[PDB]
Image: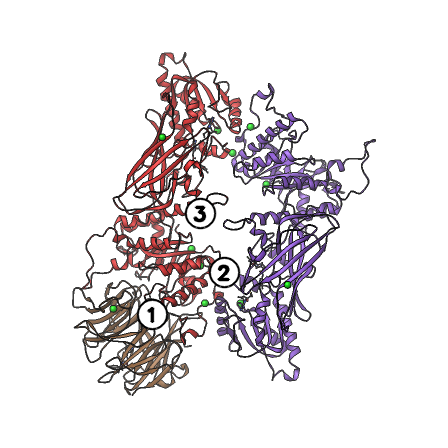
Chain colours: A brown, B red, C purple
Amino acid sequence: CMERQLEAARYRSDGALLLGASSLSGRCWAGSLWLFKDPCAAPNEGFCSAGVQTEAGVADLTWVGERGILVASDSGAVELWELDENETLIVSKFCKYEHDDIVSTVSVLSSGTQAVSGSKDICIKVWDLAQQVVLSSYRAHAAQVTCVAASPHKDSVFLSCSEDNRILLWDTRCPKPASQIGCSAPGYLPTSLAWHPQQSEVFVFGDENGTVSLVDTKSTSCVLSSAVHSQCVTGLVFSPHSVPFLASLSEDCSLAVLDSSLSELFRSQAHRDFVRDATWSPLNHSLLTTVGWDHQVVHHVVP
Amino acid sequence: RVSSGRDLNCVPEIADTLGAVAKQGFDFLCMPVFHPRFKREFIQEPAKNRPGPQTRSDLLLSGRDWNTLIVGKLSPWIRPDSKVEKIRRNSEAAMLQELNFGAYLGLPAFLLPLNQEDNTNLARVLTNHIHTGHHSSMFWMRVPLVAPEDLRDDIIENAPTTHTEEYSGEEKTWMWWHNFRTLCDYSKRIAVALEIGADLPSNHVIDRWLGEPIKAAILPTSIFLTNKKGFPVLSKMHQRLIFRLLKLEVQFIITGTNHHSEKEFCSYLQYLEYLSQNRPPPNAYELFAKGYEDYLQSPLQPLMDNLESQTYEVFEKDPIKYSQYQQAIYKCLLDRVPEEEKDTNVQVLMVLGAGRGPLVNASLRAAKQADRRIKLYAVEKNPNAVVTLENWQFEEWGSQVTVVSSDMREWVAPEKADIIVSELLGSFADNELSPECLDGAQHFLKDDGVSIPGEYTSFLAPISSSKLYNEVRACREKDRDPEAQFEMPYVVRLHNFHQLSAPQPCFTFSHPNRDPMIDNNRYCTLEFPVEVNTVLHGFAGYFETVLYQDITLSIRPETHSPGMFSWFPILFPIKQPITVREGQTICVRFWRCSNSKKVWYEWAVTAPVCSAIHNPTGRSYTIGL
Amino acid sequence: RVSSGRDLNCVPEIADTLGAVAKQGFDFLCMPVFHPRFKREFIQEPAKNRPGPQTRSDLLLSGRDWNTLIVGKLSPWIRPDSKVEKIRRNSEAAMLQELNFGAYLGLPAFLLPLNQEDNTNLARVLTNHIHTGHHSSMFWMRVPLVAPEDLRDDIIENAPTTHTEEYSGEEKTWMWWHNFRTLCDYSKRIAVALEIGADLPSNHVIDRWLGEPIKAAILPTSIFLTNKKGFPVLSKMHQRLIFRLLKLEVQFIITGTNHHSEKEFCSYLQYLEYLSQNRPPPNAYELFAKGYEDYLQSPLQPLMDNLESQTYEVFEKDPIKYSQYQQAIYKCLLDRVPEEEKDTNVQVLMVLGAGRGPLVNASLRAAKQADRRIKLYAVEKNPNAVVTLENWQFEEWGSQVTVVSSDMREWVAPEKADIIVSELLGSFADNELSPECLDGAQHFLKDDGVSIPGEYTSFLAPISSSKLYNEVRACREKDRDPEAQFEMPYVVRLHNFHQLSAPQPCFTFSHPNRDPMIDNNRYCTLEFPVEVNTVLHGFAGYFETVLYQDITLSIRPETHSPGMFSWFPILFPIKQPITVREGQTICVRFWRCSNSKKVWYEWAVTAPVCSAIHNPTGRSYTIGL
Ligand SMILES: Cc1cc(NC(=O)C(=O)N2C[C@@H](C)N(C(=O)C(C)C)C[C@@H]2c2ccc(F)cc2)cnc1N
Ligand SMILES: Cc1cc(NC(=O)C(=O)N2C[C@@H](C)N(C(=O)C(C)C)C[C@@H]2c2ccc(F)cc2)cnc1N
Ligand SMILES: Cc1cc(NC(=O)C(=O)N2C[C@@H](C)N(C(=O)C(C)C)C[C@@H]2c2ccc(F)cc2)cnc1N
Ligand SMILES: CSC[C@H]1O[C@@H](n2cnc3c(N)ncnc32)[C@H](O)[C@@H]1O
Ligand SMILES: CSC[C@H]1O[C@@H](n2cnc3c(N)ncnc32)[C@H](O)[C@@H]1O
Ligand SMILES: [Cl-]
Ligand SMILES: [Cl-]
Ligand SMILES: [Cl-]
Ligand SMILES: [Cl-]
Ligand SMILES: [Cl-]
Ligand SMILES: [Cl-]
Ligand SMILES: [Cl-]
Ligand SMILES: [Cl-]
Ligand SMILES: [Cl-]
Ligand SMILES: [Cl-]
Ligand SMILES: [Cl-]
Ligand SMILES: [Cl-]
Ligand SMILES: [Cl-]
């Protein structure tokens, strides 16, 4: 049994699609992980490569190399799952309950051996994925942590944003590791973060009002802004192109594809519910797969 | 035993989760009625037309289980006071939906958080929901003792945490409640679920919650330390706070995951039970007045009304008071009769207001103890108690006790008394008209006669208690002034309140009153220094009395007689609560007025702000002469 | 088991007597608090100065025993309505004394006799005592079913007993109560202790006590017959009366000495227990509605309000009603689809007001039973019940049932229905606005469509019940009209009342309403023949409904559906009770009024006397559209 609310979708190096779903209504509020080596067969359960039911619903996931799956659970747990040698089963490597509320976001650092997790318990934790222990726990925010994003190439640097209207840049090599960025005045609450793949000092963030903004960590100034969506921006995904595109997702049930100037180039209203996750295909850099709470897996082609 | 509940934000199956939390030993479960991450759209298509079902079915639990074991929780994404208009309206709709589903399930309580200063639209929606269908359901406002902004780690390099003392700032969360509670017009269905952090604030921040309607105390598992054997424990300050909360008889709510994973999760709860089963055992007074904590009662008027048999029974089962009376009579008998006159001198002793005759037996025991001869008159105007007095006299006392069924102010005594002994004191000393009664009886006292009690003095102290204020406000009756309940005193075992200043003497009376121009009217002005930020709601009243020399009785807290049961304190309310800042002085005025038919009190606060004069002309409360 | 007490006028020692009556099996003791022959003087010397004590001491029993086991009795020499002024004033004083001593003891009830027609001064003294201090004590008026003058032996030679039938004279004792109760202004603390004689009067004399607050029934030992084995028994008429009293759940009081002296005295009491343990066992309806007898409740408005889960649960656990609905749907499906079309014809069936879906399952069972194919729409405006509906649909029903969360008057149906099935009937048929709802839903019904129910009709019957009148009168609230409680109906399991005339149809509605000019306003005039002397206090309301052809539901008493639980009768009160004599006709008027926002009822009695028009313009009661 697969649940209706598709939560996350990630491609693998060989073109396989990892899906994470939850049941946010009905008798059971659980979740499930799935792996489709035929991406066009998703989300049909009978034509999947692997699949497992988990304890509670998943709120965010991410790959750990080519075999690991890191899951943020509603139970307050961080779970590492591993694939079978023949990649037919999804077995649990560890499941640690260190957060006191729903773990809402998780991100693997650049080395691949450590990760960072954020939860509604306002805390942000650093995990050693090999020792299955928490290296450090920080209580820097004053409200629910909305998103955390590891830097692409620095193992000690990562962004975080919470409902306390703070956007914190983190360098764990400092005695005070967090530093506040944010736009000039108290803007609308930050809801989505994404580092730039080519520029290690530049990122983008989307707020609750539908605005996507391009910021540089050095000059800490809103370099650009665009009212892209009519509702909260829940996700921001860059493309693997040399000059990358920006995929913006919102609760207005629409996907937008913008350029380096945050100008709208493509738009899809195929989903009839919230758009949760989007991923670009490594084999075909022009193919973008989106998932949503309408149990739809859409494959767009983008010029 | 403690009443405890388990807080969870993740419930896969409701039945298995409820069974697990019941096996762990919890009495109820705080859980979301909708999935916390299941954000719903009410205005904009196409997410507005999301296919159902929207949450779990109500058939998954029995109606009894919904009524007794489930506490609802508001979804964390509902922000009725968001700066965004879309989110504002959508959260209004979602909050109404969740509250209506909670009322549809018949839940006994529903949790709503207070995370910021501005909760005005939240208060508007909740007040609209309250005034929609008569219900008994409660709304617990989850309020942190310390705001998370004042609790975060000092790890933000360019935003350091303030190290400067901010006396009023550290109390900000109380304001969060006080404003909200004020916006909802002091609804009795709205209470506090106080959440406690790992680091406790100053003592004044904690004391700001004295007198507040605290129904629940929330303990996260993270605040628990660990001992040598690995069991979760608490620091001594947290133990003090737990004891203070146990005295208020609140429900404790364990939240968070099991961090002491080697031990079972019930360990946490067990610790509380431990802390409860080793709490300081209450004295005889606290056991006697357990069920009457903060229970408002009208003051007795034994002069105008005839007391019932069980009221006299309550008065009699008070051995400390009658031991003191007997000791006073013993000392007075030894003072008035020398040793060489013990056979020739027979003292005339008159019990004025004998009731069923405990003072008569006390006088007899004092005469036997002092080896002195006495002649007893037992005066009582209540004929129902005169029945008991005369049965006593025929069966035991004999001719030594002469029972007089009349008013002491009209009785024509056949002789004059060496000693008069009375018990006509109320919670506010003279509030039962002992001065007037002992004045009318003064003519048949000898020129050197003695009155026991010889003196009494009332005491007042400003208090803070939103709970008692709300109870008084609820005491509204038809066919009278809608605010008459605020202009009358109440006899009440004060429990959940905060004394704002040291008690000070109010009115003093002495007997016999040799003064030719006897005037029992009084006018007193009291200045109470207040060293905290608080809200004045009324004045507690106590009394002291000198029966004879160093033999005294007292319900004043500093000098209370240990183990005395006959008197609860009194409470004078005020119509409007008054904000009092740290360092300000509460100046209050009190009058004791009278005519030929009735006596009453009038009072008014004159500083830091003026109130209305309460009970003018005794319109709301009088004491019949 | 019965609740019984022992009546005595001679108590040597109170403790031994109480122990004896407890050993005999009695629950309480009616005894004099003063000696019955101890006449006391209050005005004239020297008997005024009689030395005490005046009665027994209150220390002879515990306060619990005084509160629970002792019922006081007025001394038989106290005649407050004597023709002599001295005796009048002295009896006033003595009655006040005894009542105050009873209140001093905290007695739960005090007995006072009604032996003559004139008890005006007795009523004055009792009313003054009632309005002196708040108390919960009860006053039982010992009233004989037959006056002793109409009960004496015909042995006076020059004063023969009348052999002529006097219909109103034989009821005189009821007047004795009715006047007294009227003089005391219908005090809730005043009830009846009906005393039964050896010879029972006509059935109308007994029925005159229907609807009266009878708390106790007094049985003398002399009225008991004796059987073959010597045990005391009662005649079959007395057994009928005992059963009628047991249905009212009164307390029985055995008075008199043991005349069957060979047997122990408990035998009498045992007989009652016998008669109680062989009383007709109640049906499922009486067991279901036991605790709700004469309990006033506001009528539900499922259109304006969203019903709770347990209300739907009460509606669902009613198998007779849903069996009838299923049979109606079965007959209709067989009527509309021939046998040769059972595979080709799929009937469109729409449940309008599905709640949690019992009618949906009834329709499915009817389709399975009739071997016909159906397509189901389940329309419900209450979203909380839509949650249950959609969980049902996802888990069991499937695509066969389409859940529609909207108002049936606004829903744009994708197709038209062969059958519409509704359950929108209240206790007064249309008092929940089923006509308007089914009118708004009429447009998506086929030209030959069927509505189940197809018809319904309300019924009214004038009733007499001083108990229900006093309850309605007690339903006075602040911040509204002091008489608004009389201008609104109440859903109530009628128990202690008297039906004065046969129920008659009031308002009738049919569906579908093909009439081009639809008007649901109604005006009805009803003439009820009354053949007894009685006091009208209100009108009971029931309903009948034809679901389909000969399949009907009914709470009308003559045609009530056996074992149906979903509906209690309704009660329309009137502000002032109306005396109705034997042979008179009660002419009443009833209106069903409405505007575009609300519907309400208006009613007035026009014969034998006119009342005020109740609930004008819906000022006190409206039904929201
Ligand atoms: C945090 C987050 C990220 C994304 N993004 C994506 O899934 C995504 O599109 N990519 C990452 C990955 C799937 N990928 C790879 O090729 C791997 C196998 C090596 C292709 C592509 C890519 C984009 C830019 C690049 F510079 C390189 C790769 C979506 N959701 C969330 N929450
Ligand atoms: C000698 C003397 C004593 C007092 N003592 C008081 O009035 C007083 O504090 N009470 C509170 C409490 C102690 N108590 C109770 O019975 C407890 C079990 C509830 C008795 C009484 C009271 C009872 C019912 C009421 F409604 C109000 C007050 C007054 N006068 C005189 N002369
Ligand atoms: C199908 C249907 C049925 C009714 N039935 C009634 O209203 C009615 O007679 N009741 C009295 C009684 C039977 N009952 C109870 O729960 C018992 C246990 C006390 C339910 C209900 C009621 C409950 C609480 C109230 F406050 C008032 C009424 C109305 N509408 C529709 N559509
Ligand atoms: C022991 S409670 C006070 C007692 O004194 C009695 N009492 C109060 N005022 C008077 C009075 N003026 N004369 C006689 N007894 C009194 C009351 O009836 C009660 O029994
Ligand atoms: C079974 S009790 C009557 C049911 O019908 C529902 N109901 C009443 N009026 C309407 C209406 N106009 N549209 C839809 N459902 C209704 C009520 O909400 C309740 O569930
Ligand atoms: Cl910001
Ligand atoms: Cl239920
Ligand atoms: Cl609720
Ligand atoms: Cl609870
Ligand atoms: Cl005593
Ligand atoms: Cl008396
Ligand atoms: Cl003065
Ligand atoms: Cl007693
Ligand atoms: Cl009484
Ligand atoms: Cl009784
Ligand atoms: Cl059901
Ligand atoms: Cl809902
Ligand atoms: Cl009409």
Labels 1, 3: front one: 3
Q: CA distance from mark 1 to mark 2?
A: 31 Å
What amino acid type should be assigned to the residue bearing mark 2? Gly
In terms of depth relative to the viewer, which is nearer, B149 or A171? B149
Out of C359 and A41, give the one closest to the viewer: C359
Write down the residue under mark 3.
B474
Q: Secondary structure at mark 1?
A: strand
User: Can residue C222 be seen at all in this image of the molecule?
Assistant: yes
Q: Residues within 10 Å of mark 3 (few under 14, many from 20)?
A: few
The three-letter amino acid code for the residue at tag 1 is Ser
Label 1, label 3: how far apart the Cα atoms are: 47 Å
Helix, strand or loop at label 3? It is helix
Tag 3 and tag 2, C-beta contact below 8 Å = no
* Mark 1 and mark 2 residues within 8 Å of each other at the beta carbon: no
Give x and y (percent) for residue C174: 69, 42
Q: Any atom of ligand 7 within 8 Å of the CB at mark 2? A: yes
Local secondary structure at mark 2: helix
Q: Which image quarter: residue C441?
A: bottom right
In the rendered image, which residue does mark 1 sit on?
A73
Q: Residues within 10 Å of mark 1 (few under 14, many from 20)?
A: many
Residue mark closest to the camera, 3 vs 2: 3
Residue B63: mark: 2
CB-based contact (under 8 Å), mark 1 and mark 3: no
For the residues tagged 1 and 3, is the chain the same?
Answer: no
